[PDB]
Image (tube, rainbow, N blue to C red):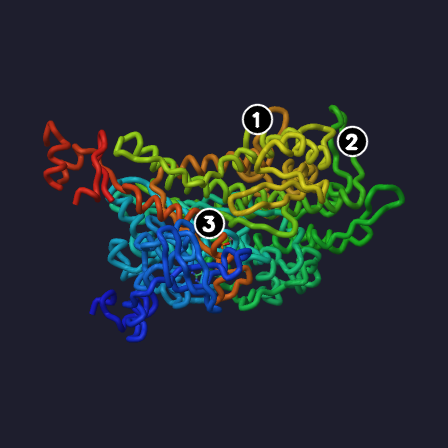
Amino acid sequence: MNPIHDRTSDYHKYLKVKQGDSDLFKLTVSDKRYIWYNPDPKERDSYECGEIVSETSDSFTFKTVDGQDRQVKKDDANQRNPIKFDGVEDMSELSYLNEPAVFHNLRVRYNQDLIYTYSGLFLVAVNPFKRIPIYTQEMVDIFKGRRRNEVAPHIFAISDVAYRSMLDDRQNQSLLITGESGAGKTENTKKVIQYLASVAGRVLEQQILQANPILEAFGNAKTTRNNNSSRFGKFIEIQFNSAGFISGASIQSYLLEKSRVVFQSETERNYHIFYQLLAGATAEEKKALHLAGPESFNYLNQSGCVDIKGVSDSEEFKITRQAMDIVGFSQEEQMSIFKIIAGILHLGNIKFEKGAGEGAVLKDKTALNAASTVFGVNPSVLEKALMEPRILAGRDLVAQHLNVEKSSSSRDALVKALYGRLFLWLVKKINNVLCQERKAYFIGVLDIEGFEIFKVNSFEQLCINYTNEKLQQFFNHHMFKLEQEEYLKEKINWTFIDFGLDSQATIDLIDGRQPPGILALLDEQSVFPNATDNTLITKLHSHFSKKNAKYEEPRFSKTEFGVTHYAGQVMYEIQDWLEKNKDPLQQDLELCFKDSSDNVVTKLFNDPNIASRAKKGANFITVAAQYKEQLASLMATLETTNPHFVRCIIPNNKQLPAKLEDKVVLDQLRCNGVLEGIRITRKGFPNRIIYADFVKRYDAEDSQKATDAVLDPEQYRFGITKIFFR
Ligand SMILES: Nc1ncnc2c1ncn2[C@@H]1O[C@H](COP(=O)(O)OP(=O)(O)O)[C@@H](O)[C@H]1O
Ligand code: ALF
Ligand SMILES: [Mg+2]
């Protein structure tokens, strides 16, 4: 039996809507009509189903749940779809396309663990927050080669469609997986990669998969929104030869959240690797590295959280090391990696105290000595580099004597540099292993850090949210703007629709050059010798307050500014932004570590690709300018691919299964442009081929006549160089 047609198969059990019973059939053939309405008009996302009992020319009257009777204009009415549509696999098929109707369909599917639903040309994936057995090899095998309409919605299906388009069109593809923090981007990314590796595979393929536990160990952490939050964005190029077999892969990582190494908010964790090393190391290795439990380290004992429900850090450590072995990190390199992790922990335990004067001293040198031992550096040199770094004053060489706060910050800067550089080094090592062939093609899978809002939002959140805004605009541009520009250019008699989705004003507020946006004003302040966080916020207010519609100068704070993003307004706290943008590290610290006896540490400080910083005239390039440039480069790459969108949707903000919260979901459906995306797919003309190229596949001087002969008139329209189909 073909599992697709076998109602006993796991495919049918886990990916198809369950058979309705005879009572549902009765309800399904009912002549009655229903409407979605709000019992409480202030709560616009909480809906009940009311029966339409009467109508006028312009209105419906319906019975509420409590049994009263309401009236509503037909043009304002959210009619409920005939219930034969409940659970439908592609929501472009719905008769009534409205918010409660789309949400209801997602809910019916979600309630039976069907997390994937097509919304026209793109896939919607609602996080189940539990394991559903739909990602086995057997599932992979079922989707292999199948057209999207032959099989159930699945991340595997869109992956296969991209793979088939790559071969059929000889064009690079991308899979763009959007979603707010914890929505499921990383999980789905991993599934796309699993699938491509299996269907296009011929050890290389295993190394591709095993890159993930490494990067997640060093790059992921518990935040309040996601127990396994990615703290770096990544674009994975899965590379193929001309025959369509996997030839390699390349990982581009984007800015890692280095600040997490030295500070975590309440209930959050540092990067997983710290907890994995401490829980998972042998008592031998804990002695050589001078390690104890998490509670003995300032960098791990501030949040009040050292464990994650359902996660064994010692077991994860074993998975991380196995991945490192498979990828090819030597035992030497692995030990050096954990020396750096241990050393960072020790550096964090250094306690600076006030000396006779304003300058800091280090009374207890235990932590300094353990760090220096594991890194292979001179402790006296390190001590002097932390508290008495030398700088130029003009051309004179002057020993500073940093006070306690500056010493502690410099120490943090060293830590963040060590961690950030190690991460870049891990990625580079992985890439060199996965770089074995010049590619013919690639499918690029984008997994950015998801849109996030916390009590305190800093520069890191602005960068993340800016990226999410840019990705949403990329969706807007491809689904709506480019689409409609093609229709109108080809004169298929298209009436332009304003879909009301445009993130450009927010993007410009952030990254504008002329007039200067936030990032540009930040950069200018960053190289202005007398700038402070206060002159910076004042500068932002001066440029944007009551001037830019997406900016708010709050009345309740002098140190925050609000950006209205697609996903909601975010208040950003300016504290430390100049320093975060400059990302300073005392040169004496680099000089100390350049002399490291450790082969990995020495690479982190001597390899120009890792250690060197690009210059913009008399200054180093800022974090913001670099960020902006890497993102612009990503977007340019994406523009050369055929994109496929997966919209991950989080069901609630508690990381709980079986708990769709309608306001949480509806906010995402709205700001993602899901309904608008379904509408363009229904009302528009998805596919078009130049007439001459259509005739040759299905020669003539009058290529249009040949096209009409071969051809229902409604499902097509003749353009000036192309035929258009539905
Ligand atoms: N399809 C899924 N199946 C099972 N768990 C999932 C699935 N998608 C999301 N997860 C759950 O939600 C968590 C957060 O998802 P993740 O992909 O890490 O978020 P992000 O969108 O921030 O990358 C996962 O660690 C897992 O617990
Ligand atoms: F926690 Al994420 F994308 F990994 F928002
Ligand atoms: Mg992630």
Residue in the image at 46% along x and 55% along y? 649
Q: What residue type is labelled 3?
A: Arg
Q: Which amino acid does label 2 sit on?
A: Val
Where the N terminus falls, by quadrant? bottom left
Residue in the image at 57% along x and 42% along y? 564
User: Is label 3 in contact with label 1 (beta carbons under 8 Å)?
Assistant: no
Question: Can the viewer see residue 162?
Answer: yes
In the displayed structure, 240 sits above or below 67; it is above
Q: Please tell me which of labels 1 and 2 falls first in the chain.
A: 2
Residue 540 on image: x %, y %: 65, 33
Label annotation for residue 515: 1
In the displayed structure, 277 sits above or below 503; it is below
Disc 3 target residue? 670
Residue farthest along the bottom direction in this orientation: 22
Where the C terminus falls, by quadrant? top left
- Please state if 156 lies on the left or on the right of 339 as rendered: left
Question: Can the viewer see residue 324?
Answer: no
Disc 2 target residue? 398
Residue 170 on image: x %, y %: 27, 40
Residue in the image at 54% along x and 44% along y? 465
Q: Please tell me which of labels 3 and 2 falls first in the chain.
A: 2
Q: Which of marks 1 and 2 is in front?
A: 1
Instruction: Give the spatial CA distance, label 1 vs label 2.
Output: 40 Å
